[PDB]
Length: 130
Ligand SMILES: Cc1noc2c1[C@@H](O)[C@@]13CNC[C@@H]1C[C@@H]2N3C
Ligand SMILES: Cc1noc2c1[C@@H](O)[C@]13CNC[C@@H]1C[C@H]2N3C
Image 1 (cartoon, rainbow, N blue to C red):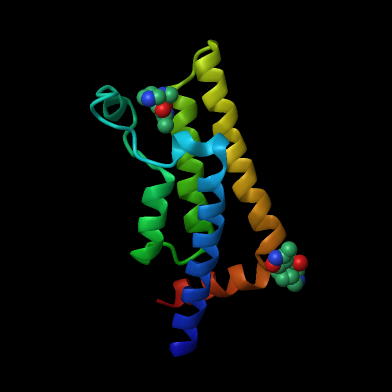
Image 2 (image 1 turned 45 degrees about the vertical axis):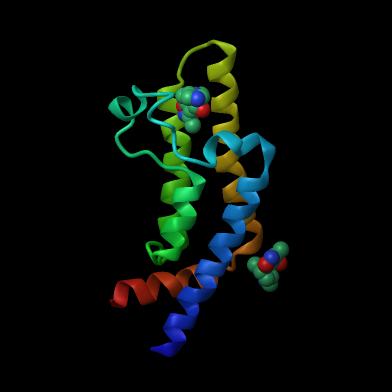
């Protein structure tokens, strides 16, 4: 229905706003673009599903996310990818792990404060009906 298409358009407006706020935070610059295969040819041999915030906006605009939960799976993948590629005790690895945990915790905190649980449940029920 038109009403259902309006619900999904509001979901995309909400997701774009959360994503652009994460992308302007200086702590999360390393997560704003895909890893450059030239600088890091080893990356795509270890990490099987690369993800970054520019890819997330592209996916919002392609209608890939029908629920909040769908979107948070990709935020969780940006974080898990950084934890698995950078697992060592040295300061460069510890700094990117701390920034990756902060990106994940920040996204979940904005959604807890600013999403209504009934809007999230409406999107699930429309998705399940399709
Ligand atoms: C902050 C914030 N930004 O959007 C929202 C908030 C909450 O206060 C609220 C709870 N009931 C009405 C508010 C609208 C929406 N919502 C989840
Ligand atoms: C994102 C991301 N996840 O692990 C890494 C990144 C890069 O920023 C990088 C700096 N340039 C290539 C290096 C691989 C590595 N590291 C910190």
